[PDB]
Image (cartoon, rainbow, N blue to C red; front, side, top):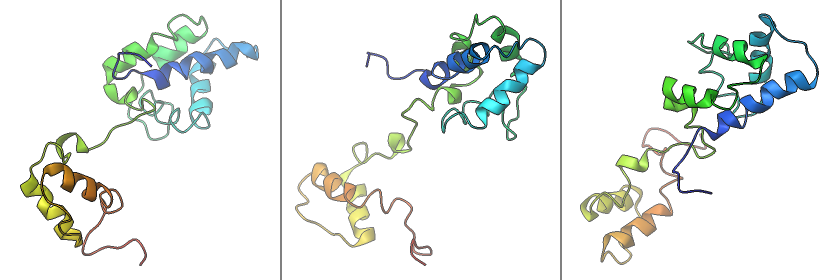
Amino acid sequence: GSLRPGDCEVCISYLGRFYQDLKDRDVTFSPATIENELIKFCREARGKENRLCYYIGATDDAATKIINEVSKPLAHHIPVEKICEKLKKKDSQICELKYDKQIDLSTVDLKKLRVKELKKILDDWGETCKGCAEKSDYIRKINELMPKYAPKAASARTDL
């Protein structure tokens, strides 16, 4: 990879091939046709190419009309790479698809916490102590049941 943490890679993986399939078939697109093509694209595109398009306006779920900023230039193929750098400024959530997504541990990660907090986790499931000398000994035996029991509660099940 590179020194960057992340980028709008899903959008440049998509806009720059979407408009290309238009002129590749010689669709002769020019009027309000172009804005329509984005929809029939976004609805079958790919699992992440179905999420970036909700923010532009090509889904039945959208709250936006910025799709017109794609219909003007597409006939000419000019901004199709840099479009994603302007969508990044509409919101980061269009780029956060990232082929990497996001998690909630960024404020509750066992490494940020204390032994006093971790001593409850194994006790809520019934694991109890297996060494209990430092935080690391808790993190590692918690991590074995942490994902499966992330949705866990007293009043719900996975096999009812």
